[PDB]
Length: 50
Length: 50
Image 1 (cartoon, rainbow over the protein chains, first blue to last red):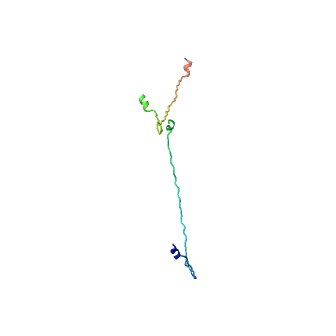
Image 2 (cartoon, rainbow over the protein chains, first blue to last red):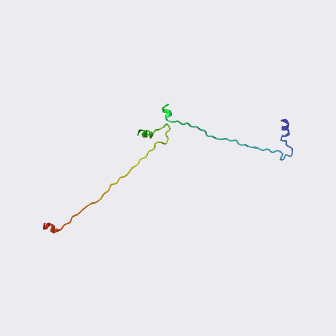
Image 3 (cartoon, each protein chain N blue to C red):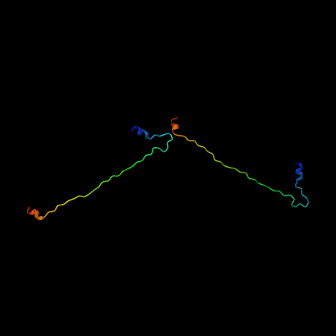
């Protein structure tokens, strides 16, 4: 918006002084790990006689 | 006896398992020993004057 930008511009006078201060920030991102698996069983007789 | 023998035969299925366990035994025997003996005595004049 033009009005908000104009109304909050960092103007400076002749005397200066503590008139405009700013700050900065950082955030963090995460991750994870998981384990999966599956198995199968059988017998010998269900292989030879098939 | 055919019934008793066929009722205790070591049959097996297709999954195995803990079945048909056996054992053994042993027995000791002994023998002995002993001593024997006997003697005879006589006099000198028995032989001379006979």
